[PDB]
């Protein structure tokens, strides 16, 4: 599973999966 | 499992998985 | 498992896995 | 398991695993 | 297990595992 | 097990394992 | 919870050229 | 919890050229 | 918990050229 | 817990060229 | 717990060239 | 616990060239 | 007699204020 | 007689204020 | 007689203030 | 007679203030 | 008679203040 | 008669203050 | 006598008499 | 006598008499 | 007599008499 | 007599008489 | 007599008489 | 008599008489 959970985000959130 | 949990993020959060 | 848990992050958090 | 736990981070946290 | 636990971090914390 | 525990870190903490 | 926040995020190339002067008196 | 925060994040190349002068009196 | 924070994060190349002068009097 | 923090983080190459002068009087 | 902190972190190459002068009087 | 801290951390190459002078009077 | 002349004469007070910037990205 | 002349004459007070910057990225 | 001349004459007070910078990244 | 001349004459007080910097990365 | 001349004459007080720096990385 | 001359004449008080530095990394 | 004679004047010519 | 004679003047010529 | 004679003046010529 | 004679003046010529 | 004779002046010529 | 004779002057020539 790939899950991103964010609360009160004022910044930058970068999530990446490369095969 | 790949999980990112963030609260009150004002900075930069970079998460990456490369194969 | 790959887990990143962040609270009150004002800095930079870099997490990477390379194969 | 690979786990990163951060609280009140104002600095730089770099975590990497390379094979 | 690979675990990083940080509280009130204003400096730089670098953790790496290379094979 | 590989564990890093830091509290009130203003300096530099470098931990590395190389095989 | 009270939040007063000024936030700026940038992700693109920025080029700026400024010239001030070349006045003859 | 009270937060007053000024936050700036940059991720792109930035080029700046400034010239001030070349005035003849 | 009261937080007053000024935070700056940079991740891109920055080039700056500044020239001030070349005035004839 | 009261926090007053000025934080700066840099991760990119920075080039700066400054010239001040070349004035004729 | 009261914290007043000025923190600077650098991780990139920095080149700085400064010239001041070359004035004729 | 009261903390007043000025902290500087550096990890990158730094080159600095400074020239001051070459003035004719 | 051939004359090609650019001539500028000034006799009055001159005030100049210039602001360039204050851009948020 | 051939004359090619650039001439500038000044006799008055001159005040110049220049601000370049204050950009947030 | 051939004359090529660049001439500058100044007789008044000159005040110049320049600020370049104050950029947050 | 061939004359190529660059001439500068100054007779007034000159004040110059320059600030370059104060950038946070 | 061939003359190539660069001439500078100064007769007034000159004050110059230069500040370069105060950058946080 | 061929003359190539660079001439500088000064007759007034000159004050110069230069500061370069105060950078935190 | 007060006499000002000018030919091909591109500059500034200031003549004054004050008693 | 007060006489000012100028030819091909590109500069500044200031003549003054004060009593 | 007060006489000023100028030819091809590109500079500054200041003549003054004060009593 | 007060006489000023100038030819091809690119510099500064200051002549003054004060009593 | 007070006489100033100048030719091809690129410098500064200061002549003064004070009583 | 007070006489100043200058030719091809690139320097500074200061002549003064004070009583």
Image (cartoon, coloured by chain):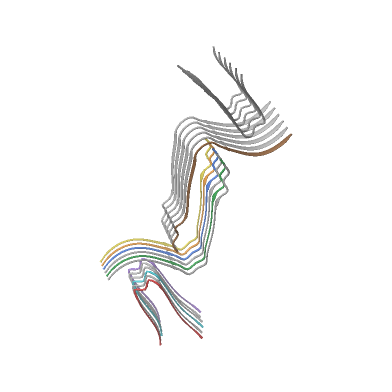
Chain colours: A purple, D cyan, F red, G yellow, H orange, I blue, K green, R brown
Q: Position of residue K9 (x, y in %)?
A: 43, 67
Nearest the eye: H16 or F9: F9
Q: Quadrant of residue R11?
A: top right
Outermost bottom residue: F1
Q: Please say if K24 is above or below A8.
A: above
How many marks the image carries: the answer is 0
Residue for point 48% across, 63% down: H12
Q: In x, y percent, where is residue H13?
A: 50, 61
Q: Residue at x 52, y 65 (%)?
A: K13
Which residue is situated farthest in the right direction here? R1
Q: Position of residue H8 (x, y in %)?
A: 40, 62
Residue under the image location 73 percent in, 36 percent down = R2
Dividing the picture into quadrants, the one containing residue D11 is bottom left
The residue lying toward the viewer, choosing from A8 and R6, is R6
The answer to whether F8 appears left or right of I23 in the picture is left
Where does the N terminus of chain F fall, quadrant-wise? bottom left
Q: In this orientation, which residue lies closer to the viewer: K17 or R1?
A: R1
In the picture, measured across the screen, residue K3 lies left or right of residue I11, that is left
**Residue I12 spot, x, y in % from top left:** 49, 64
């Amino acid at each position: 599973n790939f899950l991103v959970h964010s609360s009160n985000n004022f910044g930058a959130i970068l999530s990446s999966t490369n095969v």
